[PDB]
Image (cartoon, rainbow, N blue to C red; front, side, top):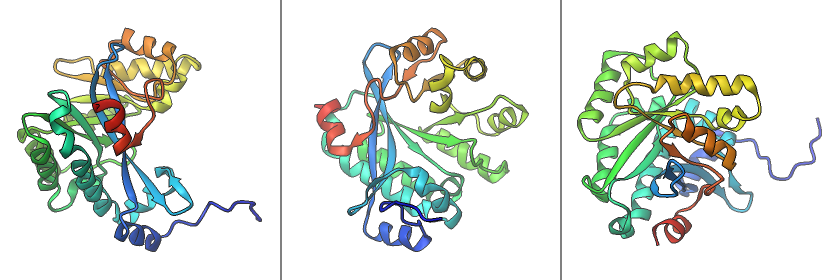
Amino acid sequence: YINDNHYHHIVTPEAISLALENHEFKPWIQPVFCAQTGVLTGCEVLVRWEHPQTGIIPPDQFIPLAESSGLIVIMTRQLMKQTADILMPVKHLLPDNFHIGINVSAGCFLAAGFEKECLNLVNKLGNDKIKLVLELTERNPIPVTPEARAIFDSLHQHNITFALDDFGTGYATYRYLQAFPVDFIKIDKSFVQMASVDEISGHIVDNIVELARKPGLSIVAEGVETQEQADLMIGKGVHFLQGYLYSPPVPGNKFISEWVM
């Protein structure tokens, strides 16, 4: 197969490792809002691989290998460090209780020192100023063990919150949530985008919302692209919106320039 393509380069573990040495994995930041008020409540940090001069490589090109290789652990550590570096100078300008969402893979969660790196980020930005939200995914789940539950529960006891990027409402999902009782349910962008278009996807979004219908739980919808989608989500009792409608992810300096100043 001959492909007319000058920008695809087979991603190898050694390419990821060198890129980590060169600090090429950068946190882009997408704002998150209260319902349809337009009030900024927080953000999500999203990795992009900025490789000279291929350009800005999206995570679907490298995260699966970063996870299988284990290099994701260093990557996430770097992302949390850089997030602190970006926001520390302007922490006083953030709204009180600004939420910061970081994606956490099973390998990162289980790695020695994980909680310490989370608490370091929080302490740098202010424990009484921001709220860290660790985003878990059903895509590749943390095995349920008492050790893993102790990590989860300790983080919960040290002022950190969790979200689940949720895709299903089957038995395994409920079992996972019993082990790891998250604070937020996230409706994946893949379903939000189809809700108004595909009737099945609409039912699945409804099923996911019903998951969060319990005391103390709230919901974020990501991938909100249109006013119709945003309307639909708030009307279902979705608390927080994120998406291209408001802003795509942007580099750190632009996030500060556009949303903090």
